[PDB]
Length: 517
Image (cartoon, rainbow, N blue to C red; front, side, top):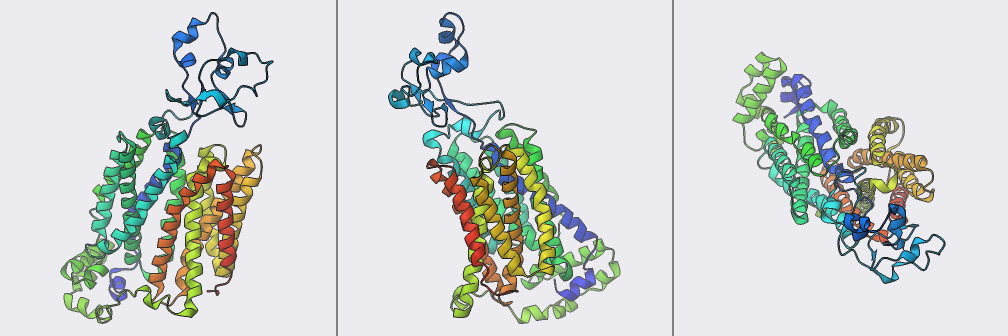
């Protein structure tokens, strides 16, 4: 509400703590939902089905016993990188390759056959996975990143429909509905019997996630006092950062693709259930002509906060008088027609959007394929969650005691350079590769939290909202475009990482031109 009314009710009190505690917790589950792909879509080694081994009758027919390692060569051509070919099989058994003396070069997939009878996967680490359930390998390999893109697409559409809708019906209503939609879609996706159904439910989950993300932040911003807005926003981000540790802790327990999704998405039922006693912001109620309900909510909060007499003395006349400043000036959002037209301000918008897109692209394109970065996913997830916190805390101190532009440029350049260096080093040293990847992800997080603050300060007060929205849209578009880059991995796994390392470096170097503050 207006500063006078909020101060009369009380800037900080019981209700603020209760609402912050209630709203921060679901953000961890939202991060868990976003990062569930690393574990519910793992790609295990997939040999080609062979009747000689799986069908016990044929194997037992041969007198004596033949070791599986020796009997595998006779029916699997030697694939690249000294391994078994992933999507082929010998047309007929070849006992000549059985003798180790003969060179295996003559034995190749030239006279082989495709995987007619299906693939055999590994259940040592993951008991089940979506890839092993719908055969998303070989010719369907490209369908894996696709499922990752559609989900992100949903987020982009969510902010396009949760923007005006929440501005007409309210904040709490949209938040509650999005909680319900998240819970229902997450519960339903676990039972999807076909790939398109799962993709549709994932897209709906993304829609609800975008709605929740916007609305919780808006509500928190409105209710908290002016002096403590950034302090609460950084906590709202720190919750999403702890979401990574939560994700790492959950996946280690349940090894499945349906149980994991169900357990992750079931708490949103409770989130919806208890989200009915949260108060609708009186600011939006009062400006939109809803006076009685806003006054009732203000009195309710005042009674909650421990000041009863102050709330009792309130009357609609003082409420109307105190809010005349906003009503007289009905600030209407200005379109881009008055933003891009001015030649002087073009450069600022161009680089701001460039930075937003660079982070939104590179961070998601790298985080989603967490396997290629290190050896074991669980340790990488835990270390990402642990390291994101100190970087986010130290960025604020750096900004306080250092310029915004140098910090932004250095963070972006360093994150990009660590990501690039991660590829060059060999695969013998897993520890160093994992450390470099973790440092790169932390740098990207720091760059995001710095640019979030930096974007608003550049432009005037009137045009700040449009520029912020443009940056968010560009970052979400980059996030969508991120996963699609992996389709170039057929040439080699190094090219996607090279692109992910080159983009942030150039973005950071470019970001050194726009003025400070």
